[PDB]
Amino acid sequence: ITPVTVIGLGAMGRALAGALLDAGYPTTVWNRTAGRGEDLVARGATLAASPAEAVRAGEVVLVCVVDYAASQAILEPVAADLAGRVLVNVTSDSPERAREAAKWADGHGIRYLDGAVMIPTVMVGSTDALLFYAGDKSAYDEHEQVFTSLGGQSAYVGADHGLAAVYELSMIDFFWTSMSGLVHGYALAAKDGVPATSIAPFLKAHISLLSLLIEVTAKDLDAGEYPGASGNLAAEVEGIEHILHAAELRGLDVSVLRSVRDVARRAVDLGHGADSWSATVEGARNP
Amino acid sequence: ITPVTVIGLGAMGRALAGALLDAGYPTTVWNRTAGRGEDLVARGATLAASPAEAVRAGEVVLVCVVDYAASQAILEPVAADLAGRVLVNVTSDSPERAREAAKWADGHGIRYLDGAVMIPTVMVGSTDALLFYAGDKSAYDEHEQVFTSLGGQSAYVGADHGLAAVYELSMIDFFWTSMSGLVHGYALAAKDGVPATSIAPFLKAHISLLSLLIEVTAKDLDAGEYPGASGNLAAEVEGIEHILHAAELRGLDVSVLRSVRDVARRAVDLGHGADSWSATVEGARNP
Image 1 (cartoon, rainbow over the protein chains, first blue to last red):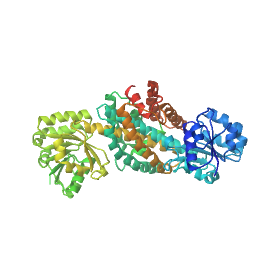
Image 2: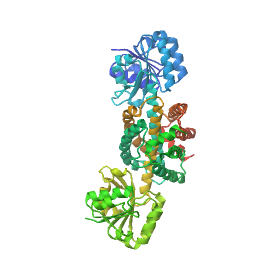
Image 3: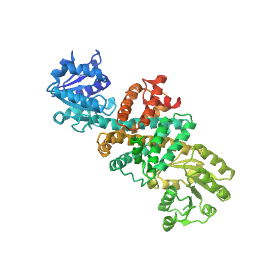
Image 4: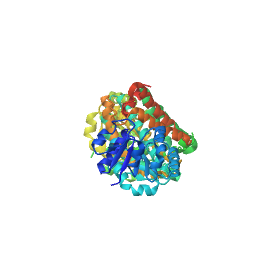
């Protein structure tokens, strides 16, 4: 029933618009460049002439313009049409940008939600898809089913509009560093003639291990106490130096491993040699 | 039931001997430092006086010392007693250290397996526990049940004795880099007043994502083809710069993320701006 507008038809905007069409919502789409939305119009979407007209077609307005200046130059001149509607910004930025956008929106009577998409664009709309939301609570609760359609696992994280980005930046810090180590381990093995698909089945043993450490590292971090009950940081530093040694011998770039080693070395230098790996947060905070 | 000897009663050695006692094997143990194996002796193990006596008590001899020279300094004076037996060296080395030990074993007629333990000491003996072995094939197959008692996910990875270390260093490259990013993501959040255990439940969504990328990166890596069907490296570099800048704004050490950015940046400069994340292996190989 509820009409929704998607402004910006890049990859993200196209995927978001597709999810709304799948769920059965009337969808209006606007793109600066023609032909981005033709597949969606063939699937039932209505293409709008102007951003102002697009805004007027929706109670919920998703903005998916990736560049900041362009997004602001589109939204601010149509602030009067946005009043009384729910504006949802889905692009990945910084937590401060989300609060500054929040301050603009309430000066013009716009209920504002800042969002973060946490899954690849192909997974948008699935039950498993995770999306973070922060801002006006009544806006999220009123149109909860719309956001569930974009993500089954989509979650609200508080009224402070920067909290979506905080949650987002915390997870993708973990994700991209892990992907860096994933590629690097495969490279290290490839230097000894082992195919990556020979290692891949065994990396599921360390995936389930990682899942356990996620909770254990979280408790130690909030407690400010790292037990070191199993293992010790000084030994963990040593094992990392073995990976460094072998990778440097094979001619690989080791700037990441050196940085991982150096932050842990800092924590050891601050007296945590007997503590668990969680104690490396002291090295990260005190460079 | 085959008699087994465990030489070296550090954390790893005590656990390996414990798993063998749990499974019901006749176990003989030896440690340089007194009182290390009293708990094991109370559980049925027999403490040996000399390394030679320990060796003579076992058809399979596990060595669990810390340094390879130390392992050799115990094994070379008792090389005559090991002849005709199966020697399993479980200590963490380099693939080259393991290949040199292979030659010494051959000179004395010892079937030699080099091992790597992939799970925490507390998981040794469990069904899910993974252990890598490389070397004499008939030695692994004849005493396979012995090695599955150390870890039900035990895997023999080939006749090259350095392959156990190769697989090991490849996996813990991924693991320790991930733990570095895990601690760092938690730190970033804590700077905005979000407790780590509020974020931890959502990190299970990104672990399942990581599990998927493990296979995709492996296929991409062995194929030498990096199709960025969804996403692209040039955009992924940009998103990482959002985390980097936001993290140094908050006074955190960002050397890991900077190095992650730079390895991917190198790959972009090598012409892979349109390729997937898998193309960052080119940055790792050509620094």
